Length: 454
Image 1 (cartoon, rainbow, N blue to C red):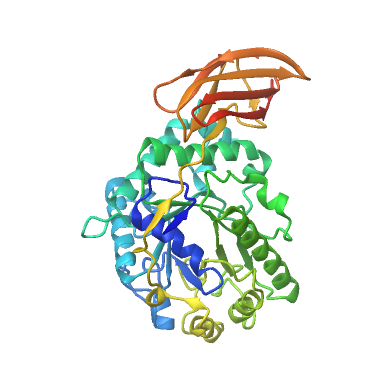
Image 2 (image 1 turned 90 degrees about the horizontal axis):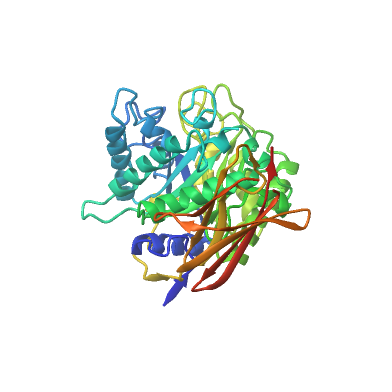
């Protein structure tokens, strides 16, 4: 008789099971993950989603199979540039099915590449993809494709395969902070929240768990770590991304402090924490480094701490080529150490994953939430009128009013109108604090955004 807080209160049985399993493993063993593990290999030859350098070097597949949404764009195998998005999606789904059949857990991340030059969201492109933005439609279409992938990731018997989905994280560099998100955390929060709401509430995705990791190297400082946190109603798995090539005592101490911190925050929230990304900076190949016994040193530091060890998985990077790869292969100096890392009883691989999906676990009722999607907290409004959008979720809503104040004086009062799909809205012609008050079946909910007018 188990009940858990899960972002999608309507998630499938297997999905709720997975979230329970990931919490339960914390401190008992840590699942080893590898990105594109059956799609890019140095020892596999041509890939088909059934073989892996990890299997060849350790004797087992990883417990976690990582993938990028980049595959849909055909910018990452098994995605092909020459393909229709629909067939890149079918391939993606096929490899996810194969991983599930192997016994692994799937994670899918959406990086922030599209938010730069060559990217399709390219316009301060964070502002651009939010509701009302010049590129909002691109975002929505990108999400539609993700919803398509979600629905296609089904076992032969039709069962949806649960996926740990990590929307909008930075792929550079060694600490992986998304500069735009730190620069405007309110806008990051609205982007993440919309992403969750569009997929869950608008598209009906029911096989996602939602991951968020803001980077790494926080010195265990919680307020820095939480700067871009989307909120308890929006995140299932709390992450941490840290690459290092020194193997130093100092680095290890810093890593342990952060791992303790995320486990502590997870525990307090009744959530799951995971070491979402780890690896040798620059990889362990030609263009990388071979810090001595780096894998077993990292693992021993984690194991030695009863709180830092409370982390569900740790995923390392893609094995692209000799110059850039993150799992050692024959010829690499770190091969033996990685094998030892893999043989350690604390690290879990595919054949050690059991009871992940067949648990009986009910969802706690969704928590009522109110947030102002536009203008986002800390944003700057450009034109008048601008549209105020408020999302009230998880309860029935009778009305929403907005009070606009400046200094401490109310300057405007707005009665919002439900748009029939997602938001309560009203025009606003500025101008500094924007407070939404929703009258609902769960009581009166409010939230305040602080914004600037041009």
